[PDB]
Image (cartoon, coloured by chain):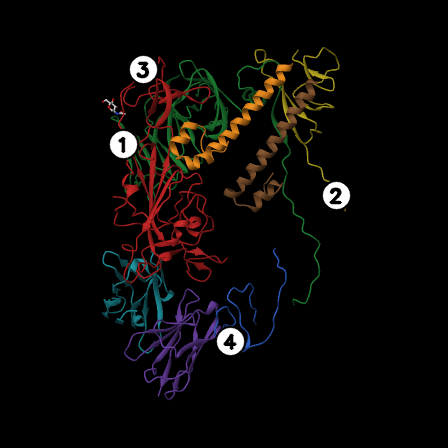
Chain colours: A yellow, B cyan, C green, D brown, E orange, F purple, G red, H blue
Amino acid sequence: EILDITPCSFGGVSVITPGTNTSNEVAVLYQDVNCTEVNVFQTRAGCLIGAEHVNNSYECDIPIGAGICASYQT
Amino acid sequence: QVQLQQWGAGLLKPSETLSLSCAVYGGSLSGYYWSWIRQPPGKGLEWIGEINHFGSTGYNPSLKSRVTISVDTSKSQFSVKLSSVTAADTAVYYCARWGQGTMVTV
Amino acid sequence: AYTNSFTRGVYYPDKVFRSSVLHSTQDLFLPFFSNVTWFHNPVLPFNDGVYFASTEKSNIIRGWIFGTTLDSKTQSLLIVNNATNVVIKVCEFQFCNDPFNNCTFEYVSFKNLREFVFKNYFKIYSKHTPINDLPQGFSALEPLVDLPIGINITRFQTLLAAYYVGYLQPRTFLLKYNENGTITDAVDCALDPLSETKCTLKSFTVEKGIYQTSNFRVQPTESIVRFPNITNLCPFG
Amino acid sequence: FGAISSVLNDILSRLDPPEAEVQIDRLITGRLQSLQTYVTQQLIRAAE
Amino acid sequence: FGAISSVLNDILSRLDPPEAEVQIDRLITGRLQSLQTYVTQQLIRAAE
Amino acid sequence: EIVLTQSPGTVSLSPGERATLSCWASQSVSASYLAWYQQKPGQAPRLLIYGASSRATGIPDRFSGSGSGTDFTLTISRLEPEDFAVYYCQQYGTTPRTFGGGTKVEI
Amino acid sequence: EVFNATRFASVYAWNRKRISNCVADYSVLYNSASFSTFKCYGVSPTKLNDLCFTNVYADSFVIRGDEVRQIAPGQTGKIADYNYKLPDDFTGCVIAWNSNNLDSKVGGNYNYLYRLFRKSNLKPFERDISTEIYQAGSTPCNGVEGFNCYFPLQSYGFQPTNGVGYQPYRVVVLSFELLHAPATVCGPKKSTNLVKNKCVNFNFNGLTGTGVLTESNKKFLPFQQFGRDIADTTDAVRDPQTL
Amino acid sequence: DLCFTNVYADSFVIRGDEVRQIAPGQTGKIADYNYKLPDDFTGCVIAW
Ligand SMILES: *[C@@H]1O[C@H](CO)[C@@H](O)[C@H](O)[C@H]1NC(C)=O
């Protein structure tokens, strides 16, 4: 049996946030994973938690990656 | 120098108790293991009890719950207290780590 | 019972004076918003250290006893206050079930929130505030006493009407000494991602943006051993 | 980098704690320097 | 940086010289690295 | 429970002859837990061999012990005029330390 | 007293005498070559009574002569593994000297033991006076001492005729801790008066440094010993002799 | 779980009294005239 070896998933964690002077609700980015090994969105840049994907389009308030940007709004 | 003098023996009525004396000279009873050895007339030796120097002590099954051995570091003396004596307990008790022997008649 | 430990459980980790500076450190503390036991007698462990806090209206609380066996067969620490001074000693007493020798050391000196923190060697941290259940807010516990016994202690029962029990853990905090030189606010580092961020920037305010704080890593679920294919038996037998 | 081995576990496994950590100090100073060279080149190659 | 303390005056006050050089050298090579990192940063930012 | 079987019960021998005392245990005695005692008539027990191979301190070299497991064997290569006494072996491989019945060395 | 003490305990049952509120000179501990072993590790042996510490421990016992090697920072060996272990960051000195002239019965001392069995080596400054029989084998060692049940506690045989490598040595180790709390002992160096506004060399309760001394308006808190700076460097100190 | 370069297995039969005599430092007719075991012998003997 010829067995491939992959160093299993691991990545940096980043916190999305609007300014503290505005709110406390925050979102977490997990960098490049399926995120079934961690209301949940999936990017070509990583896994996003705590934010809602929206079909709409707007200017980039906070960059994420691959053209996805996050913002705080109704 | 090194001598172990036994005392406390004698004739005893059945079911009574006894307390052995074993005066040691030149030895540190609390620092070396001590045991008491009996021998009924015409028999071999029978180990009854032994006391570890640190304080641990054990008794043979024939004397279990009836014998109690302790030491007076204040006098460096070995003691062997037996209770509920009987005819079969008649034996010559010499204390060793040997002593001179102490005949017990009961 | 249970209650939510809002923000209490802080204390000067040493006597060093500071001023208007956010300092990051690491010691035992009561993690924010933990389940504290609510009482109305029994004996509880002391695996690391208790955040003890009692509301006091009739001064019924009188002390505590700490140790492993909580009787003879070893020593244990005692705190008593009897109307005249605080009395402390480390003897092996004939402990009763809940009353209200061979020892080396002894010391003798519901709005009343007599708060206390005990950690191990042995320390004593407290605070006394006017109050009016457990209130939210903030308050720094000042050190009171260091006691040099080094006794193996795993368990305690109080010596008495209510009080709460916490439990300390090795987290890392961010403490804000004030201008006067006082802890006025602190933030847990591991409570939540927002908190995790604040420690990274060493601040209490975060401009809208992105911040990388920690590293995700799948921990290996287990260690699995593979032994090679056996060779052949030779005339040993 | 003058340590007994490139594998960290090996140093952890083979050598005693009070002695092994001397070897680890070599690896840290070794690698940690290497990043600085890497990072520094990146900055210059970035400002380029 | 691995020496037994961070205060240069302390490490002297507690040791006579001959093994102090074992300790102090650990600081020197530590801090001395820390500058040139800072300087190089400043140089790089200087050009920008 | 370890009962030491000494044989023979009596032995008559002349000086200079080799005297062998046999000591068998009802169970195998680990690590040669066998001690030899020689008891002169009207005299206290006197240790001869410890561990079945180590002779006591000051005991003559004529004394010798042998055997392993369920066999212990005491040898007196050259009999002595004061060697005609009772020899009792003691096994201490179990908590119930037990001794043998004793073998009498006759003339 | 602790040095001229008539008696010592075992290595496993090693005394831990706490020391506080002293004026230590150590001067008698330099000239007196009576200590065949004197190896300061935390600090320079010469420079002690010029320094001082929050608290100091006097651990005392008597061991075999060769074992003086075993008591070293991170040293390995049975006594070190089963009887007394030093801290890796040992802060102090070790004092040991021969005790054949005292610790020797003419027939040999049995008085001093050592625990040669333990399933887990002690932590530094750990002290396990446990007396229970050690299970040597894998059998349930149920109160029967002997085969597979060996006694961990073994005594030194200290006869005057033994070799020096086996000769009894009296040993006392001092451990220090230079911490934040006020020191309890400081060496004999008489203080002087306060001076203001001058670049001077100072040394407060052992804390050393140079600069200018000024009164401050700093509102310490009644317990607060002193402050520091954002560089983790000293900012202000309180006179011991004046708040 | 370990292993050496080579293993040497001997075989013979003795009398029961001779079983004691195969051990490091043993003295006996077997120990001196038939088969001796050196002091620092890495191995052991099996008899039944
Ligand atoms: C030393 O004497 C002064 C003046 O009496 C006193 O204030 C001080 O408390 C004494 N010692 C210390 C360091 O407390």
* Viewer-proximal residue among G213 and F42: G213
Residue type (three-letter) at the residue carrying disc 3: Lys
**Are labels 4 and 2 assigned to the same chain?**
no
Q: Residue at x 34, y 64 (%)?
A: B49
Q: Are marks 4 and 1 in contact (CB under 8 Å)?
A: no
Residue A54, x across and y down, in percent: 73, 15
Mark 4 lies on residue: H32
Establish if G79 lies above or below F25: above
* Residue bearing the label numbered 1: G188
Question: From the viewer's perspective, is residue A30 above or below residue B17?
Answer: above
Q: CA distance from mark 4 to mark 2?
A: 59 Å
Disc 2: which residue: A3
Tell which tag, 4 or 2, sits nearer the viewer. Answer: 4
Location of the N terminus of chain B (image quadrant): bottom left
| Picture quadrant of ligand 1 | top left
Among the two numbered marks 1 and 3 on one chain, the one whose residue lies closer to the N terminus: 1
Binning the other alpha carbons within 10 Å of mark 1 as few (below 14), some (14 to 19) or many (20 upward) gives: few
The disc at residue G196 is 3
Viewer-nearest of labels 4 and 3? Answer: 3
The kind of secondary structure element at disc 3 is loop
- Name the chain letter of the residue that bears numbered label 3: G
For the residues labelled 2 and 3, the Cα–Cα distance comes to 76 Å
* Picture coordinates of residue A73, whole percent (x, y): 66, 11
